[PDB]
Length: 274
Ligand SMILES: C[C@@H](NC(=O)c1c[nH]c2ncc(C3CC3)nc12)C(=O)N1CCCCC1
Image (tube, rainbow, N blue to C red; front, side, top):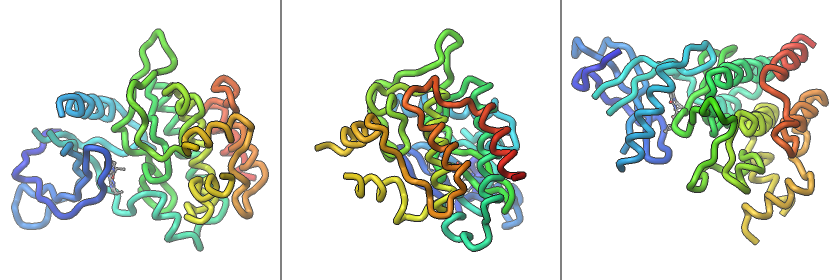
């Protein structure tokens, strides 16, 4: 669980995003190109470093088949398993022809259990989106990107963030947009949007962005008015009705009226079997 920097050998960039990068490296103590591939996160500020230390301790404490696996650290860097299939967003866009409704329901279920495990750990993810879900195998996904994750204090069930969110606005719960309030129930909001991503196969032309522009002053405020009015994303083409109903349930105006991940899971399992 401790990796010497000199044995970690740079290959390429996997991702870039707010103050950090993920790289493909080979952990290669023999120096001969035979070592295992790992994904390595690092920062590129005094506070981001503190947040980074917290992100590591959170992921180190997580153990689930549906959460990207922590491998160790190097001292400054976070070492993780490397999933060559990349993110679900690109996987969906590429393998559209092979993934039927069941597969999509299998993914949904797997993400759901993962989120149920996070909630049980008192962890709010804050950035659930298909781009942050990694693909382990054609029938297995894992939640990643804990850079924004917060631990809820025992006394509270919500968290308030001082500075504005830097992710696409179309994934945020209304109370996050208006008051910077994040909770396990704002995660359920974002999960509804992830479901929408799965059943559109993250098609760009019917993405949240594209759909918002079609429904029509600051964009953040417009989106708020639309959601306040009860406007919502439409059923993805060929989307099963029961699955769309689940989205709308995740998109309940008030966080208390959104179902828990533990309630959702059973329902997704039944639809998967249905
Ligand atoms: C989502 C996050 N990825 C990870 O933490 C990964 C862990 N093992 C992986 N195997 C393959 C990949 C492919 C997708 C690039 N990613 C990962 C990431 O890339 N980013 C972008 C940079 C900032 C953090 C979020």
